[PDB]
């Protein structure tokens, strides 16, 4: 039994339908997330380019999901927005019910469970998205999670998804000290990212970023989706014209 | 004739068969019992290790204070079963006070795996599972295996997943049907060596979880599991 | 032939039908729009079946809200009905909850939410139309948006869709700067639209409107301070051809 | 060409043609609009000597003023009649006044209509003749599988329709003022016999009904008994 | 084949649908008066066993709106009904009688919906609605099976479309207005029959045709007799 | 278009069931002519099977048979080509519907087709009957088996006649049947009265 | 693109239904030329069937026939290649839609195609008519059956004419019909007026 | 991967629509060269049809024709092989999608393919034109029909030229059309701009 | 099982993309060797087309060409058989899944396969180049056309070289492209990283 339908099972226990989608990912912009013992980093390279496209009073790669949680997309634009929406809702029901912030582990799980849902019933196709989840909860502190359309999630030290994430992947395996303070990461981010590009060079416009950090002076957690400026600048700091 | 909800000439439902082919694709689990314990062993697909040790998952799962289970096959699936089981575990206790019988539990689980093989427009769980525990106010160790089709079965010791066939053989000529492994200590000793076939060195790929009566339970630590690899390689060299 | 026809993943990852929908798009009529610092402009050709049809009874640039209008290229019918529901959702799911009308961004997304439904579901073929929605709202200022049958959407500065896009998108690309006032745009639009024609170029044969400024006249009432007027302005057959002078 | 909903490269629904094809294949039915009221007749085919005569009626009344008959697939016919029966009786309860034949047809046409729209359903396999009276006279129509029907001066379907057709043709001209209520029957009696000459080796039983304010008294009655006999004999003489 | 996109996005069932509208074999034409409107359609009665009363491709939808359809009688009677009731439901739900141009919208709307959701096969008929509403006067809008309507200053549906058409077009480049200059309907009627006869290389008796007139809120079908008298009228004056 | 139909018309107008009815009827009784061409070759194999040796010189009665047979193949083939002509002229406008009638036409053509092919693997055997004997009658200077091979080349060719004849009868009869059944479909392949829907 | 269309244009512009109408019309009456090439070969088999033996030397009336026949095959083939040319020039852009019209074109090409093949298994039989006789007229030194084989090689080749002619008429007529019906689809295979949906 | 693309690059870079445009254009007017190779062989069959008998010795004007024809087949085949080259270089990565463009390529290749085959059943007939005559001019010692067979082997081969030429024109023209329509699909078979979904 | 894998291992280990890259690269520039083998045979047809008659004795420059060509076929065929070897060694376990990669392998093999076949209908023409001339140079005792047939058998064989060369270039180039695109699929036909589901 070959290709078609998700409800089909190949003679060897394979769900092709899935395996295609689970691979469809290799078409989206390279997104990366990294962990540090003081903050989490989400880096991403934009796609769909031309010269007549804004991106400032919008985004489409880095979405803030909770005041304490964030995600990096890499799949079908149409899909993502749907999950992103119900992911936000549910997170709020947790708040409205327990009057407390929803734990990252939990949130990731529920989502992976919907993606999995569409993986087993006739009349619907699986979501073709991949997410890098980054957030904090006082239960297990900082956390970097990931999930594919197969509905599996994973704890990572620092990961990438999308394009060339095999190449990009290995670059990471080299430089990474577990404690590695944030700036070294933000820096590392670009280093890893530049190296894996079809553009003549890395231009701010075609790029997305954000970070998470918390402390004693904040007493709580603060996250920042970086605006057009800050980027055009830190880029120079890492020595880029 | 493969897209099952129909019969082969010889009366087969090939889909349901193929699904089992995935449980083999997956990781590996093995359970053993004594006259006081029931140990559950599993391996660890330590493959792309650049991920936090801490919070990332581990095969054995508690379903109620006195019962746990393990699997092999699709993780993606497995999770959903565990959840639905855990739920029924309470729905019972609520509407009946008395906490669940391990036999009952399995039957419920198997009923679900069974539900996903009837209506057209749904596909079977690519998961086979081992469920162990001790009944309420009871000291008789219980071991059951459930698989994709919907069949449940009680075993003295069984294994599933890739290379189960092997270790199974091993077990077959080790586990004494007449008398089960007495002490807990050695009941473990057993299971551990039975996994050493597929492991390929390192207690870094071996998970042990132990269950006693009166809702006691307890997973194992790495060194603990190591002090066994040790005290076994020793007697292997002594043969 | 392939694993195309049906709503399911092709071996790589390409979703079937969807692309053939984006075909009825490319084949369809030529249309454009330009966001321009103090106004925004959207236009499309009005290629008449025959001169016996008084084409004067069929809008292509249509009013979504007194601050938002949109346009298309592709399957005529899809656009007609898509619009009406689109208007309602802008009410039921916004105005009746908040008292006012919705910002561009959201109404678009809301339309996209509908564009979505038609996909994730067997038994329903998506829409054969891409929409160019242009608008404004007190907090985000002027906006430009494209919406494909695939649900997805993007924020533009200006662009075109349809037969003459490869070309137009290049002409527009050359003629754009960030300080252009509306009349600059308006002018510029025509000159792009110029090439993209095969038929005529007079008034009644060009559909164009724009989002500009408050029309205190158009209301019908007077006495309320904050309620001042729609920005959406469908230029009529007259106002046009006159602007044909400065080329 | 194999599904019911679909269209052919140049707009054609084949399943409906075959529907028609089966309608022809069955027995032959007719009907005639006369002075005031109508007259129907069908062809019951005695396949053996073990059939009780005067028994299996193929003609059915609706309300208490509408004659009705058909041919093709017998159960399909019966089915269709039921719907017509509800519609009628519902209307009646609603407007009080017995249902206008003109509209009735549509109610049915509309129902036969549907079964040409979806693929999950099977086209109606029968052509149906019927009529009745009211205030503004008697009427008579004939519904096909396509759902298209009309008003005729007399109708015919099933096996030999032409026989009765050219037969109906004549009557028109010699009696361009509507044939006598009475003569209508006996004439119908003949028109059948003539058209039966295909199942000639196999004997048969003729069934007749009619409507008329003068004869039936607004109602639909089964032509059985004495008038029934002579009407046969009448046919039996011209049968040479 | 089936109702979902071709490789060049043109799902033919909708296309095929069209030939069948045409296939019936009748010619329908329509033109505006000044305080009335008119449509011409042929009335070919083959079977000498039927009854011309029961024949027609034009029906009285509303007190003022009429409809003609070049298309297969079963499918038409359907469209006829729904539309006939949409207006019925409208006047009730809104306080004022529904105009031409609008009915044609929910109508096209309806045929679009079907088409996209797949809840049935499209009807193979083109509906040509006529009337005169006190907002836009002499109104004429047409709709096809591919769910779509628009406006005509005067139109035609049939096996021979463009012929009937071109004539009117030429008669229009000269009369230069976008309608028919004239006060009486009888007179307009005369005019169309005229422009059709000329257009077919054919002549019609008093039963071979079918025509309707939309007035100042009182739409009526032209019957057998009155119909002939217009042929009387337009015989010498030619 | 006026002139165009006239041709397609005057063509179908000069051939018809009227014409074909005579081939079926003509090739009905004419089988006697074959049931004869049979018995002749038979009586003849006995004289060859037993008319011991000789000194050669072309047998007159044998050519009398091949001439009579090659004679028949000729008639038949022309007669078939006539039926074939009547059909090819009725092949409707090519399209993807009503192809039920069209199909019949094709199937029948393939069988007729076969008939013609059968009359051509032996409808030349006279110019071939005496084609192996000039090679056989030569080598006039003697294998005592070569003398016997001449006895055979005479009887062998008489067998081929009897046999071709036997099969042939069958083929013809088959064709008769085949036509008689379908035919109306062959001339009227599309009906088109189905406009009872519009 | 400017220059590109011009070629496809000036090419279709020098051949059309206008041209093909004349082949159908030309090969309409021209069948007489074949209904003739028939009767000629017939009258001739009787003289060969009965014009007892001889001493050889190339028959003038026979070559008069093969020359007249091979002459006709030539005409027809050129005339067909012209119709074929008119169509191949109208084969639209290859794709998987509107292939209804395209299909017709192909079907017709396959039938025309056949016609051309038919004119080539015998449109050479003159250089072959006298090709077996140089082998037959030699061996001038005598089988009394070899003398008769010469009587046959004359009559056999006269039969092939009559027969090829018979079939040929049919093929032609078939083609006439086939064209006359479809044709409009052959030149206008796609319409494309269906933009009443956009 | 750096070096790998360079090759695929510099190869497609030395052949293109630019190149092919000249074959279509080149083989556009060049048909005159064939419309000529025609009329030549025609004028020639009349002299052979009527230039009564002889005593042999290789005709100079005839080889003038075969040399001119065999000459043309050569050109064309090289010219086709060039168009063929341009496409084979554009066959995309093999897979089961976007095969709409790829399909076109194949279809066109099959037609070109045909053209080349046509130029090879006769693109050798010179070394064959004089290949049957050494056998024919020998047997110099006399069938009075053998003398006439030499008259024919000259005219027969002149007919084959005229005919091959007639068909050929057609094939070429077909190909011109076929290219001019598709082409863009031939060089750009996959687009891939469909990433407007991700 | 320990030993079994070792074999499959050490075999794939002695051939690879590393090897094949050199054939594509080797047979990249080496086309010059063909673009040459071309121009040589051309300059040579002119001397044969015009170097009027003779008295025979084996042409030295001609064998210089066939030796050079037959020489090339040899190289290529060995070089292809090497690429073939590299793939057949990578055909995975036969089953009904992941056959996307396997498919590629097969398609490419069929094209390579073709190349080898092409080099064998002419890769022997030397032992055949002088194979028709011993028959041609004999009959040394005179058709004045036989003399001319020797002029042709020389030029004809010089044309076959030029032509085989022309096509060949194409085939090679095609193959270059085809490999360069797929290749990675050719060595890695199954992936198997999809265990992200278990
Ligand atoms: Mg349906």
Image (spheres, coloured by chain):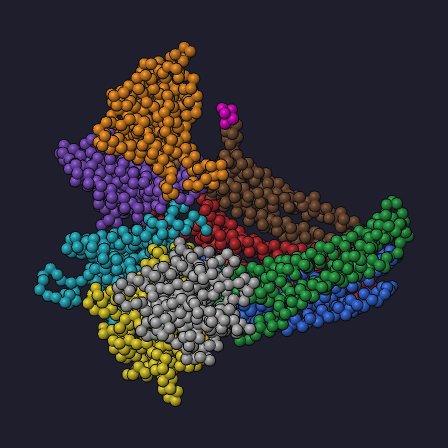
Chain colours: A purple, B orange, C cyan, E yellow, F green, G blue, H red, I brown
Residue I104 in the image, given as x and y percentages of width and height: 49, 42
Q: Nearer the viewer, residue F2 or I17?
A: F2
Q: Is residue F51 above or below residue D129?
A: above
Q: Nearer the viewer, residue D170 or A207?
A: D170
The N terminus of chain H lies in quadrant: top left
- The residue sitting at 24% across, 27% down in the picture is B99
Q: Nearer the viewer, residue B148 or I69?
A: B148
Farthest-out residue, front: D226
Q: Is residue I1 left or right of residue G172?
A: left
Q: Which residues are magenta?
A: I1-5
Q: Is residue A187 visible?
A: no
Q: Is residue C81 visible?
A: yes
Magenta run includes residue B64: no
Q: Main secondary structure of the magenta part?
A: helix
- The residue sitting at 43% across, 64% down in the picture is D70
Where, by quadrant of the figure, is residue E42 drawn? bottom left
Q: Is residue F57 above or below residue A176?
A: below
Residue E132 in the image, given as x and y percentages of width and height: 27, 74
Residue A64 in the image, given as x and y percentages of width and height: 22, 42
């Amino acid at each position: 039994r070959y290709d078609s339908r998700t409800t089909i099972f190949s003679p060897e226990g394979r769900l092709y339908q899935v395996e295609y989608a689970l691979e469809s990912i290799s078409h989206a912009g390279t997104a990366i997330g990294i962990m540090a013992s003081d903050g989490i980093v989400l880096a991403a390279e934009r796609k769909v380019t031309s010269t007549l496209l804004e991106q400032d009073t919008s985004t489409e790669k880095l979405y803030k999901l909770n005041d304490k949680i964030a995600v990096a997309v890499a799949g079908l634009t149409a899909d993502a927005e749907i999950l992103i929406n119900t992911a936000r809702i549910h997170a709020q029901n947790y708040l409205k019910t327990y009057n407390e912030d929803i734990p990252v582990e939990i949130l990731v799980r529920r989502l992976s469970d919907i993606k999995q849902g569409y993986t087993q019933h006739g009349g619907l196709r699986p979501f073709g998205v991949s997410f890098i989840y980054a957030g904090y909860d006082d239960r297990y502190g900082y956390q970097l999670y990931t999930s594919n359309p197969s509905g599996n999630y994973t704890g990572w030290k620092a990961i990438s998804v999308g394009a060339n994430t095999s190449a990009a992947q290995t670059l990471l395996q080299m430089d990474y000290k577990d404690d590695m303070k944030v700036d070294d990461a933000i820096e590392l981010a670009l280093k890893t990212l530049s190296k894996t590009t079809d553009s003549s060079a890395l231009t701010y416009d075609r790029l997305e970023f954000a970070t998470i950090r918390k402390g004693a002076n904040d007493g709580e957690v603060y996250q920042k989706i970086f605006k057009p400026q800050e980027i055009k600048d830190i880029l120079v700091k890492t020595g880029i014209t | 004739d493969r897209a099952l909800s129909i019969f082969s000439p010889d009366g087969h439902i090939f889909q349901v068969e193929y699904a089992l082919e995935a449980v083999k694709r997956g990781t590996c689990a093995v359970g053993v019992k004594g006259k006081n314990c029931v140990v559950l062993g599993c391996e660890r697909r330590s493959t792309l290790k650049l991920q936090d040790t801490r919070i990332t998952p581990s095969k054995v799962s508690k379903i109620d204070s006195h019962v746990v289970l393990s699997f092999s096959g699709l993780n993606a699936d497995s999770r959903i079963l565990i959840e639905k089981a855990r739920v029924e575990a309470q729905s019972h206790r609520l509407t009946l006070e008395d906490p669940v019988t391990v036999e009952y539990l399995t039957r419920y689980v198997a009923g679900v795996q069974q539900r996903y093989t009837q209506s057209g427009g749904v596909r079977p769980f690519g998961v086979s599972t081992l469920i162990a525990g001790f009944d309420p106010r009871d000291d008789e160790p219980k071991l059951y295996q459930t698989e994709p089709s919907g069949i449940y079965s009680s075993w003295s010791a069984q294994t599933i997943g890739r290379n189960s066939k092997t270790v199974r053989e091993f077990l077959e000529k080790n586990y004494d049907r007449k008398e089960p492994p007495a002490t807990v200590e050695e009941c473990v000793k057993l299971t551990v060596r039975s996994l050493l076939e597929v492991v390929q060195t390192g207690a870094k790929n071996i998970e042990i979880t132990v269950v006693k009566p009166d809702s006691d339970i307890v997973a194992l630590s790495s060194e603990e599991i190591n002090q066994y690899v040790t005290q076994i390689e020793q007697e292997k060299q002594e043969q | 032939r392939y694993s195309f026809s049906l709503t399911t993943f092709s071996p790589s990852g390409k979703l079937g039908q969807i692309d053939y929908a984006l075909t009825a798009v490319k084949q369809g009529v030529t249309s454009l729009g330009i966001k321009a610092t103090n106004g925004v402009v959207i236009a499309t050709e009005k290629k008449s079946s025959s001169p016996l049809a008084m084409s004067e009874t069929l809008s292509k640039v249509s009013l979504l809200t007194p601050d938002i209008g949109a346009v298309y290229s592709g399957m005529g019918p899809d656009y007609r009905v898509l619009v009406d529901k689109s208007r309602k959702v802008a009410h039921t799911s916004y105005k009746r909850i908040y008292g006012e009308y919705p910002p561009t961004k959201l109404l678009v997304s809301e339309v996209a939410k509908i564009m979505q439904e038609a996909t994730q579901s067997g038994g329903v073929r998506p829409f054969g139309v891409s929409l160019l929605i242009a608008g404004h709202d007190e907090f985000n200022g002027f906006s430009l948006y494209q919406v494909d049958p695939s649900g997805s959407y993007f924020p533009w500065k200006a662009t075109a869709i349809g037969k003459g896009s490869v070309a137009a998108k290049t002409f527009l690309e050359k003629r754009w700067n960030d300080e252009l006032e509306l009349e600059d745009a308006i002018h510029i639009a025509l000159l792009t639209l110029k090439e993209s024609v095969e038929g005529e170029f007079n008034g009644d044969t060009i559909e164009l409107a724009i989002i500009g400024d408050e029309n205190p006249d158009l209301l019908g009432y007077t006495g309320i301070p904050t309620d001042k007027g729609p920005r959406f302005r469908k230029l009529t057959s007259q106002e046009i051809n006159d602007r044909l002078e400065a080329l | 060409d194999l599904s019911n909903s679909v269209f052919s490269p140049d707009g054609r629904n084949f399943q409906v043609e075959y529907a028609v094809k089966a309608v022809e294949n069955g027995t032959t039915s007719i009907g005639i609009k006369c002075n005031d009221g109508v007259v129907f007749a069908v062809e019951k085919l005695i396949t053996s000597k073990l059939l009780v005569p005067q028994k299996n009626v193929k003609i059915q009344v609706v309300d208490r003023h509408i004659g009705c008959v058909y041919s093709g697939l017998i159960p399909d016919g019966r089915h269709l009649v039921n719907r017509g029966r509800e519609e009628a009786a519902s209307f009646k309860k609603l407007y009080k006044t017995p249902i206008p034949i003109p509209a009735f047809a549509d109610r049915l046409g509309q129902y036969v209509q549907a079964h040409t729209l979806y693929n999950s359903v099977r086209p109606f396999g029968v052509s149906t003749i019927f009529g009745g009276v009211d205030k503004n006279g008697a009427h008579l129509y004939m519904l096909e599988p396509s759902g298209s029907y009309w008003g005729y001066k007399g109708a015919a379907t099933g096996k030999g329709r032409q026989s009765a057709k050219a037969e109906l043709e004549k009557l028109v001209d010699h009696h361009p003022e509507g044939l006598s209520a009475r003569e209508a029957v006996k004439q119908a009696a003949k028109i059948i016999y003539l058209a039966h000459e295909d199942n000639k080796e196999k004997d048969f039983e003729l069934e007749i009904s009619w409507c008329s304010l003068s004869e039936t008294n607004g109602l639909h009655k089964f032509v059985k008994g004495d008038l029934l006999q002579e009407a046969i004999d009448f046919a039996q003489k011209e049968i040479n | 084949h089936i109702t979902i996109f071709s490789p060049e996005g043109r799902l033919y069932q909708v296309e095929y649908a069209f030939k069948a509208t045409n296939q019936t074999n009748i010619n329908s034409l329509a033109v505006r008066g000044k305080d009335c409107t008119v449509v011409i359609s042929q009335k070919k009665v083959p079977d000498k066993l039927l009854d011309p009363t029961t024949v027609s491709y034009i029906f009285c939808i509303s007190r003022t709106i009429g409809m003609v359809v070049n298309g297969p009688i079963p499918d038409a009677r359907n469209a006829a009904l729904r539309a006939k009731a949409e207006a019925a439901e409208f006047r009730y739900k809104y306080g004022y009688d529904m105009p031409c141009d609008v009915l044609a919208k929910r109508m096209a709307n309806l045929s679009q919906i079907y088409t996209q959701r797949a809840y049935m096969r499209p009807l193979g008929v083109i509906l040509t609605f006529v009337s005169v509403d006190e907002e836009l006067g002499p109104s004429i809008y047409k709709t096809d099976p591919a769910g779509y309507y628009v406006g005509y200053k005067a139109t035609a549906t049939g096996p021979k479309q463009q012929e009937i058409t071109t004539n009117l077009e030429n008669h229009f480049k000269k009369s230069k207005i976008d309608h028919i200059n004239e006060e009486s309907w009888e007179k307009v009627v005369e005019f169309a029959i005229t422009h059709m006869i000329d257009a077919l290389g054919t002549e019609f008796s008093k039963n071979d045709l079918e025509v309707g007139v939309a007035t100042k809120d009182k739409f009526f079908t032209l019957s057998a007799e009155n119909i002939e008298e217009r042929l009387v009228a337009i015989a010498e004056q030619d | 278009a006026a002139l165009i139909q006239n041709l397609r018309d005057s063509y179908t107008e000069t051939s018809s069931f009227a014409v074909i009815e005579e081939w079926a009827a003509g090739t009905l009784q004419e089988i006697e002519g074959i049931a004869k061409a049979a018995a002749e070759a038979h009586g003849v194999i006995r004289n060859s099977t037993y008319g011991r040796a000789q000194a050669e010189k072309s047998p007159e009665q044998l050519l009398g048979v091949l001439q009579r047979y090659q004679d028949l193949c000729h008639n038949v083939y022309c007669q078939a080509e006539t039926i074939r002509t009547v059909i090819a002229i009725r092949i409707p406008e090519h399209k993807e519907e009503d192809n039920l009638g069209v199909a019949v036409q094709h199937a029948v053509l393939k069988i007729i087709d076969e008939l013609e092919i059968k009359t051509l693997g032996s409808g030349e055997k006279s110019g071939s009957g005496g084609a192996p004997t000039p090679i056989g009658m030569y080598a006039l200077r003697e294998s005592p088996s070569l003398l016997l091979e001449l006895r055979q080349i005479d009887a062998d060719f008489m067998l081929k006649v009897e046999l071709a004849t036997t099969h042939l009868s069958t083929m013809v009869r088959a064709v008769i049947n085949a036509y008689l059944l379908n035919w109306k479909k062959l001339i009227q392949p599309r009906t088109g009265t189905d406009h009872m829907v519009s």
